[PDB]
Image (cartoon, rainbow over all chains, first blue to last red):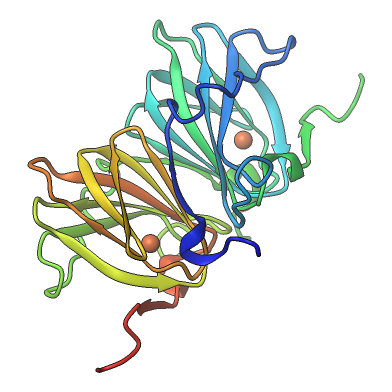
Length: 137
Length: 137
Ligand SMILES: [Fe+3]
Ligand SMILES: [Fe+3]
């Protein structure tokens, strides 16, 4: 009645999701993403994954969210802000972001910064995401 | 006293783990792996990730495990066995494996099949893994 087990094995790639529009927000010019493994699209559970592109100059500013997260960097170079301490990331790297850790990603290179993100959640839309500032002045 | 939050953000790559020996087993010639994000090495939690290589001809035979899993295919081509139904996978694909789904991976190509795996567990060593057969005859 409901797919489970091997009935719910599937393969995705960007071509698979050609007819899903890129997601983006006015506040983050130069950042766009698509959802590849997500319960709002697939019915999967336990892990969710998307693919993101940060154009040159793009900036995903300091924030945090309760679940742990992984980035898998597949192209380009970026600057990871580990709550003040900067580290370069590049193709071939993976990144672990502990739960509730303040972090940000900036592309100061000339190529697009491309990466997957993964959460231990059924869907992205369950993630509670907050700006790091938590004050007005 | 214990790192948490942004203190437990880190970046890994294969060079980072150069001094970790490749893992392999006599029963699976042509399969080897390393652990990149794992509580037995890093203290991370919530998600764990490794990198695996399946040489030409290598075969990760039919099995299952209770947590859901993702593969991120970074090079080569393989055959994913979805409990009897075969599907090709290749560079640029992601794979969702539902919890307890019987699955296997074979490299019938000429290049190494290279991929990350991810579980929603603190460590690989917590995963209960079983051969699919569950009978002797
Ligand atoms: Fe994040
Ligand atoms: Fe698996």
